[PDB]
Length: 500
Ligand SMILES: Cc1cc2nc3c(=O)[nH]c(=O)nc-3n(C[C@H](O)[C@H](O)[C@H](O)COP(=O)(O)OP(=O)(O)OC[C@H]3O[C@@H](n4cnc5c(N)ncnc54)[C@H](O)[C@@H]3O)c2cc1C
Ligand SMILES: Cc1nc2c(=O)[nH]c(=O)nc-2n(C[C@H](O)[C@H](O)[C@H](O)CO)c1C
Ligand code: SF4
Image 1: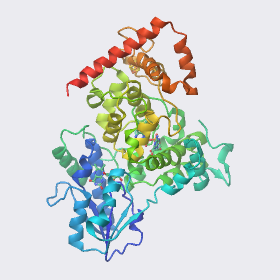
Image 2 (image 1 turned 90 degrees about the vertical axis):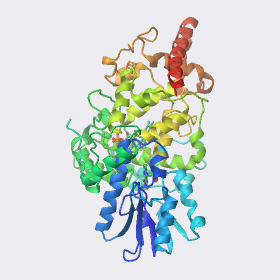
Image 3 (image 1 turned 135 degrees about the horizontal axis):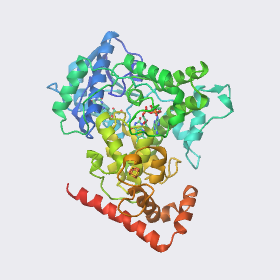
Image 4 (image 1 turned 90 degrees about the horizontal axis):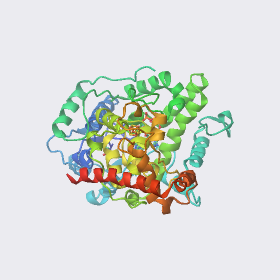
């Protein structure tokens, strides 16, 4: 007999751990355990989504003739951790070996590495076939290459998969090329019970549970993918970086949550976009861009995470110590852009790429926040957030706390960028055209202060040469007044964070 452990982000009937299962003899284990629901203060909607999808996935496996041992969060006898439930199901089932698909967190991986010793039974940890590249392949692609960039990896993924390839050439001669309501799925009985249970057990957690609309079945997630292809995929590249106060979704797909937990397969999503391309329903730039986000960025981020090692989380290139601002938890800031995106995050457990990078992340970058505080908040607030995908985006891409290890440039931008790409300023109490004075957008002074105080470390970064040139053309008193303006704003933040 076999004990097949399946984690909350492994909700696919093709997950590796299921290869070679004897439906008559083996038992699948799913457990809602407190260790996983509390290692960070997850968004209420995140906990609700995961538990619901784990429950529906349990029912689905039972529906496919699998034997499933489920453990709910408020079940008594619940041992509170993966290992504990592993003990219970062992004693229970006296199985011949444990089978599990490798996880997406160093924390969980390490626990699971402890199984073979803890139980004195052979543990079979299987490589997660949901990723195009294994750890060894990513290591070997990166080995020797004195600079990591997503692009090169992406091209190797394009060749590997055959997506948008005309044999050995990229479709359209080049690898690279840079509204209706979104679907809502009404909570069924299971989901409503979960929502109630979560609100009961995690009432102080970040976020609201009101208007939960997530797909929690494979079918509904496939319906969200289909709705994306039909309604938004055609305009996906045309608005990738735009923000709108009245529209939190725009042409984004909102599929990450399903992809990241096994309700959708990344490769199938790409094939959907490609199929749409050939049938004429989307331009090549939008479909290439879309796919590049999945077999490029997503795959590359996972590779970076496992390559950098667990202490990657400690990266602090600029040696920041400042605590996270209080308004990331409350959204009560006069900065309209930050108030909108944070409020959306509180309400919806979602924000699109450019929001995470250029509003809340950009702010945290310019403000010199302890990178670890930033990683923590990103991992908690979004229902697509797991350390393998969140951490490289935060440490590497947004915060540059790894010093550019993953090839990106510093994404520091002023109120000029945000005014240019959004309509948040239109109703903000701050003036983004003003950099000094009490009405000045905080991002202007903060942008220059960031560049100034980190000048030694960013001196030789070609991308910032124009800004430094401009810095150097300002009178000394202008540079002084800007830095002081920044310091006064940071003061206000540090003061607010003292009440703690
Ligand atoms: C600070 C920060 C934190 C982030 N944290 C996460 C996270 O915890 N989980 C997560 O899945 N994504 C994360 N991203 C990437 C990106 O913001 C989200 O994947 C995207 O907003 C998800 O919504 P969507 O599915 O509508 O994306 P779309 O705009 O529809 O893009 C298509 C798909 O590509 C993938 N994708 C796009 N960009 C990235 C990226 N930078 N890294 C990895 N995959 C990407 C997603 O699977 C996404 O569903 C983060 C980015 C930043 C700057
Ligand atoms: C909140 C939460 N709860 C559970 C759970 O009860 N059971 C489970 O298997 N997984 C959960 N997850 C996902 C995991 O904690 C972890 O992030 C993934 O296993 C990473 O591979 C999360 C994020
Ligand atoms: S003005 Fe500065 S703060 Fe007010 S919204 Fe535009 S950018 Fe955000």
